[PDB]
Image (cartoon, coloured by chain):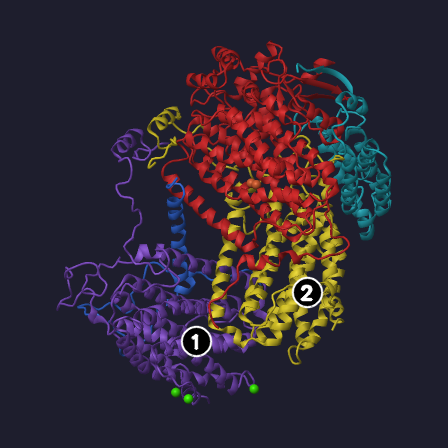
Chain colours: A blue, B red, C yellow, D purple, E cyan
Amino acid sequence: NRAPTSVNAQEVHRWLQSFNWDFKNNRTKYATKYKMANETKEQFKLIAKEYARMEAVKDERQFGSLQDALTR
Amino acid sequence: NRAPTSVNAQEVHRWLQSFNWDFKNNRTKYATKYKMANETKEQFKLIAKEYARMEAVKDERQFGSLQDALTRLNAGVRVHPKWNETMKVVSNFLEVGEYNAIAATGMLWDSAQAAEQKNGYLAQVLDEIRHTHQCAYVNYYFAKNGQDPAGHNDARRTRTIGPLWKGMKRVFSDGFISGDAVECSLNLQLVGEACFTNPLIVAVTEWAAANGDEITPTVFLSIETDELRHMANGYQTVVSIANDPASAKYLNTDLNNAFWTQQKYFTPVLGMLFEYGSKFKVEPWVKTWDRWVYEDWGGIWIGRLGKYGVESPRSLKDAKQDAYWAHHDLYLLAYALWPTGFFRLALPDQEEMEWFEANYPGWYDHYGKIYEEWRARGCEDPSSGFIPLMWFIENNHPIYIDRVSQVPFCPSLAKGASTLRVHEYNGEMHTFSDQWGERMWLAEPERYECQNIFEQYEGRELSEVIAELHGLRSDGKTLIAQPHVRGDKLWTLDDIKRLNCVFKNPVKAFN
Amino acid sequence: SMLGERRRGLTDPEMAAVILKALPEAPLDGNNKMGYFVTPRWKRLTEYEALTVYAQPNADWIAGGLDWGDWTQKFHGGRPSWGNETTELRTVDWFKHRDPLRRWHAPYVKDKAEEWRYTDRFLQGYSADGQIRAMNPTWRDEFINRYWGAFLFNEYGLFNAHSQGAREALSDVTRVSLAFWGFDKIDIAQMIQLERGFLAKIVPGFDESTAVPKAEWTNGEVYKSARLAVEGLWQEVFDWNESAFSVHAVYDALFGQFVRREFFQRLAPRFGDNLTPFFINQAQTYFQIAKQGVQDLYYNCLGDDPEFSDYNRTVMRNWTGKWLEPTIAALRDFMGLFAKLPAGTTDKEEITASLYRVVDDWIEDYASRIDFKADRDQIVKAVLAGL
Amino acid sequence: SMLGERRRGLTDPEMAAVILKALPEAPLDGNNKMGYFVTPRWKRLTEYEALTVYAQPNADWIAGGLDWGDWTQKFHGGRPSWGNETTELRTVDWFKHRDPLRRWHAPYVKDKAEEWRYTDRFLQGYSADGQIRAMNPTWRDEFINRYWGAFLFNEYGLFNAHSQGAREALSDVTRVSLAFWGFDKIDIAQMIQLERGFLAKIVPGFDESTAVPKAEWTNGEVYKSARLAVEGLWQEVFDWNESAFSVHAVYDALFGQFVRREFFQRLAPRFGDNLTPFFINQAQTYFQIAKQGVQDLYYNCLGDDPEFSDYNRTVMRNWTGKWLEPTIAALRDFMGLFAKLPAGTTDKEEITASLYRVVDDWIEDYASRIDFKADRDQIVKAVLAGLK
Amino acid sequence: KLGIHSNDTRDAWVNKIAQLNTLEKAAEMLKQFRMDHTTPFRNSYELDNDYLWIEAKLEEKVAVLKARAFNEVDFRHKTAFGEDAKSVLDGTVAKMNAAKDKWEAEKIHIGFRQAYKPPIMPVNYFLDGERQLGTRLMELRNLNYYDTPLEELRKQRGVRVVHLQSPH
Ligand SMILES: [Ca+2]
Ligand SMILES: [Ca+2]
Ligand SMILES: [Ca+2]
Ligand SMILES: [Fe+3]
Ligand SMILES: [Fe+3]
């Protein structure tokens, strides 16, 4: 089957939680009275590439307005 | 040496000319009298990818401004009613010019034999596609965010109802693609773009800005940044055939025919759209026209082609003679036939009449009095039972359509040219408004067989033609076109049907 | 001055006041959708369709046209600006075609621009990283420079084959797709030269001149039948649809796909060359992009036309048969190139498998669409005779 | 309503008139260049420099700072918000660094976004073209899935080694560069998983779960020393410069470059794999981009500092020696992977030459810049001991 | 039933072409349609407003029939009448190059179109002729284009001047 296929951010993010591994010194370097839970999750399922794309789109509209119409 | 290295467009373009090779049938597929030199070069050393990048950057700014700031400022709405209507015509009519230019340059691409010259035309092919979509976007934006989307949203079909469209197609559609590739090049680039479109585009942004429209300037100014490549294409076209002996024999004639063709339509039409389709004025069209045609094009631009055997069009003085009142004469006809448009028109207000008289001594005594007469009679009120065309019939002022240019003319009333030539040939009548177009038809009758609106609509009742060609707004009863630009008292299909206006072919009065 | 002399209607108090005073209370029509009368191909009308469909001023006498009357100015002789007489194919509506990728000018240059800038970055990293050190010298100075470079003239020829179509296309949606198919071809040709120009910069004695690859193209034996097939599709075909169909659904789908994917893209890696595959990745991405458009025009629209389905398929099977022969001939002359590879590079078993991949993909994506009964074994067998 | 209720000063007749009336006849100062006081690295001040330099509110007691006085709120105990005490390196001005690529946020996300959209186009073209058919099954299921996959954890660890620096960097230009070096590392780790996810869609039976690659990384032998080194660089280094320097100018420059370029990029093509190289091309592009920034900060700015050149080089040579040993160990263990390949894939001579390329590039681009006396044959001989 | 795109006259011809079911008859009718209703030399202008659309609907019938009747080789090389495309093409081009003047040239070209416009002649040969014929026609017409005064040019065209009006 040669149907055009790809992979999105959510599909990769699904495995991101498994990226960290255990070892004796895997702990925060800063002083703190609290302990952040080891399996805490995040609301948005982003990866570097997709984060960049969504911000790049915003920048285009913003700078376009500033350089063109607003300047005119 | 592991220094970061790459390759740019110029370094590749360096070998572009060698891309083409020789072989028996390697020649243009289109009929032509000229021979483009196979070693012709191009001014801009571009490759497909760099071309894309430079255009993508422009799109970024343009669309960014439109979707963000301009939308936040309600730029699509805070525009004078008259100009909102004018842009329905300007953007869509120019769109077809951009669209046919695609096919035109494709024909030129096929005509060029030198790889570089083909590449130059190719860059324009893509540019004209961009321009088609840009003009379409202007109408798209005004339809989505403006005060009156009717017309902006369906001009591609509603434009077929009126007579101004026919002439537009002659100079911006057929004139660009039907004929000797070189002739088309002269209509499109040497004349069309260098003499009119280029200056026009900028001028349009000036009139737009004066009337509250910041949308058009955003798009049209971006389009303008591409025109230098097209000027070069036109200039290079002449350079390509300058050596060919046929050039000395045909160039100046195709050019003169090209010049007359383009000016015949824009001289009256552009001036009309600017002065009558706006509230705030930028500059009198008589002044503008003189600078464009005589000073910039007829002088500087044409002069630089002198070394190539190019001469000023022999019909130049004739054009200047016919020009002065041309646009004023045309608006009378355009307004008289307002129900056939896809936009709303307005009569000049008091301040405007003063402006016209100040800039065109004698305007009031002719056009001014007529407009006040039509208005007092109720041409703006749907219960009056009056449309200006009736006044033309009553006062025996027939309106004709030039068989060649498709430009409407009324020699009986015109303050400008009033010549008229009528001929019959093999069971068909033909009407001409000038000696240049008359010669064109006589010498090339098979190139000009366009049916005019009176011929097509003959015997048909006005409201039926409108209904059939979808000249109605969403409610299915109110006309898109209107004789005023106010929000109340809009004319409906019924108001028109009651007029019992039936089209007649004016030429039959000579039988 | 700081404020400038020009007064703008949107910001000037006096002018803006006048404008606001003339405005209606609400829009004079609630239908704010441009192109609302266009028949959507998908759920809802897209920007692609609104901005493109019906831009071409065709009258009703050209299937699908919304205008009326003859053209205003025609060619000396009477030939119409655009007419049904420029192509054998017939349809109930020339505006039905739709690019599956919905590409109008903006998205198109946006995508190609990204490719240009990433290409630049790639080359700067490749050179800085010294990856050229692991590339087989013979493969570079001989197969990339001469044979790959020669292929640029093939793409360049298929590019020009689109010229007449740019002028004769009978609709906007078809003209746009055609223009993009052709522009992508010239891009590929220019990318081949770009690689050769890059090699010239990082490899002391490499010559970027097109003299060698051109002579190979014009006089060599490997591309002889390839060039003849190209000179024909380009300058001997006057039917814009035959030109586009035969170039994309026949020749480039068989010859082009074999050379790019089954030869250079398949062998370059074996010589430590990841540079050439970088560019072939583009050519293949482009090929698969155009393919979706070619399929929609000739099969979904024309080949399956409610009124001329039978007629069109007959014409295309006719064209398929007409050009399948020069294509197979091109593939045969190309087979001779395998004998110039160093011993052990590939075997007749692999090539046979690569040929069936191309042929089978072709039959699945093109041949079977118009019910063109083609025999994989005979074709492959016919080509293999060139070894 | 069509016009809306909110009146805007730019377009509202009454409000704009009030505004225009209050405007001066001309600007109250002709110097319209923001950041005019910043010393330009190049001919003229760049937008990159104007929008970045001096954004960090450091006082003069932190080299190069323009403010005065102590921080307003410090840590319990007294530790300053930012301070000289967070790194062994010293300089005349922490604001001297310049990213040679001049990347501020906009240009940075613009390029990565282009790479993302093109990547998506590539995969749709690759899958539709059926190029997976010619890929060697063993290479795919064993080397890409398990070994290339396990490498994602290496890049992930290096990404995390940048967290403290994001917090402690002593200037804006260094913070931005460091953030971008780190962000590119997580991106590469995610592209390795992306490829595995893609293969799972186009190859029936291929499992995208990270379980196998993770087990290889955490308990296998091939990456044992690599993981030990990464765990150290990440969590045992509290000096933000030691971290960035040792990661980019030692460990990644040797181990990273060998694995990415001399193993996978070099051998994948031999097994009909054009997919992995597509992603490695991005990784190498990122590596070379970061190198320019790393060289500018550590060699141009610190290693050549007019006042602390000798001191800083002594420290960096110390760090190079400290981290070269664990890096050689990582490479030594990785040599074990060559024995897993099908016979005839490569041989000792090819492997040795590839090691020398990596070592020679490292000596040229890094070690020599601080006068670190590296012995290239002794380093290679130490690594070759790992060949099974 | 009157109309611009839909009318009785158009409906009349669709029911007419539908009756056709033989390439011979179909082709013959098309050839005769172009003689009676197209070009400035048409036999009459009675169908001026609908002839363009009708011709197309006629070409379609001829096209379909021609594809089902001819074999692959002929569909590409012969006219719907049986003539050898290339022969006709080379012959017409020959006559055109022999033309002594523009009046003769224009007659050759126009007639060519009326007789061999696709589906009659294969598009490839047809457009190739358009390329050669048109070139010659223009070369002859555009030579000293403005030499002949309008009064004389009108006589040459043979038009019947019905009215002339010129204040200048
Ligand atoms: Ca071990
Ligand atoms: Ca060996
Ligand atoms: Ca030594
Ligand atoms: Fe344009
Ligand atoms: Fe242009």
Residue C235 placed where, x, y %? 73, 52
Left or right of B21 in this view: D70: left
Residue at point 38%, 50% (across, down): A58
Which kind of residue does numbered mark 2 sit on?
Answer: Val
Task: Please name the residue that numbered disc 1 is placed on.
Answer: D257
Q: Quadrant of residue D215?
A: bottom left
Does the residue tagged 2 have its C-beta within 8 Å of any atom of ligand 2? Answer: no
Can you tell me which quadrant of the image ligand 1 is in?
bottom left
Left or right of D388 in this view: C299: right
Residue D251 placed where, x, y %? 37, 77
- Mark identifier at residue C359: 2
Q: Residues within 10 Å of mark 1 (few under 14, many from 20)?
A: many
Chain name for mark 2: C
Question: In this rendering, do the residues under marks 2 and 1 share a single chain?
Answer: no
In this view, the residue farthest toward the left is D77
**Cα–Cα gap, marks 2 and 1:** 41 Å
Chain name for mark 1: D
Residue C167 placed where, x, y %? 66, 44
Which kind of residue does numbered mark 1 sit on?
Answer: Gln
